[PDB]
Image (cartoon, rainbow, N blue to C red; front, top):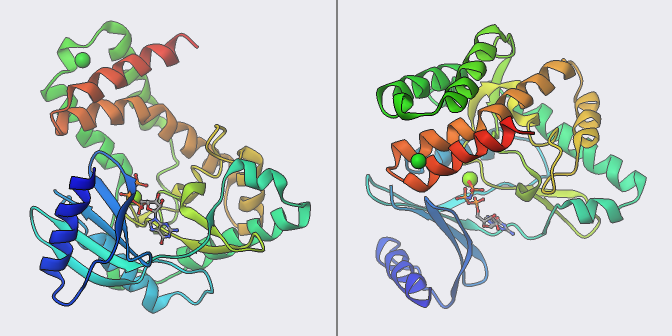
Length: 294
Ligand SMILES: Nc1nc2c(ncn2[C@@H]2O[C@H](COP(=O)(O)OP(=O)(O)NP(=O)(O)O)[C@@H](O)[C@H]2O)c(=O)[nH]1
Ligand SMILES: [Cl-]
Ligand SMILES: [Mg+2]
């Protein structure tokens, strides 16, 4: 922990010539990556990995050049990208992350203005000509098909009948659906309320973590806004945002979300196979049983 910070302080000062670290603390952390707050002013995201930060950096650059908006996003001042190590540094966007608790304290009018701000942001981003980042495409259906092939080549035959049926029933739905055939555009693609920042009037002031962004189905950016869970605000919130956003089939957006949710245990298994992490394989398989029995 105090050791973790030291290594990273060392790396930051080694790769960024005149940068002096006076303070550094961990502010966020997954199984792939760690984020640090440095000098109480800079966020540094770091990853020991093509699975690095080149695309994410290209997207910040494209967005900072082409969006016209008052909503802040990361603006990369420092970067180091190699095969084994990636670092992005940018000034911290100040604010309070949106949560369900906070939303519930807001007045009706505050909630509306927040929704309108979100809809506006998404409309502007989805309307950009993405020619200049055209290499950042993501085909979710094809990705799933390839992940299924990887399953068939590795552990599929050791799975139980219940697990196999869950997977085959998902593949059948994937084959019948039309929700991947609509408009493609640049999406944030991890658009949950823990990535939305509010200012002191409860208005949207910033958006972070475009680390999964790319050119993908328009429906992608409504997946968490439509989610019913403890972490997200609720389906009505997403529905209202969709009405404000306009010119989009809401029932398809919901079908897209439902499909991505059904995929989740399989995505988890596949993550464990690819990263040689048995814990994830086991968790995904257990989750299939939990869903089958509800
Ligand atoms: N206030 C503030 N916090 C930030 C900012 N950038 C990152 N953070 C904090 O650092 C955490 C990690 O940043 P994030 O980009 O989401 O990292 P990640 O590796 O992509 N995590 P994940 O993909 O799992 O959401 C965020 O959850 C948030 O707590 C920022 O500009 N402002
Ligand atoms: Cl297992
Ligand atoms: Mg991220």
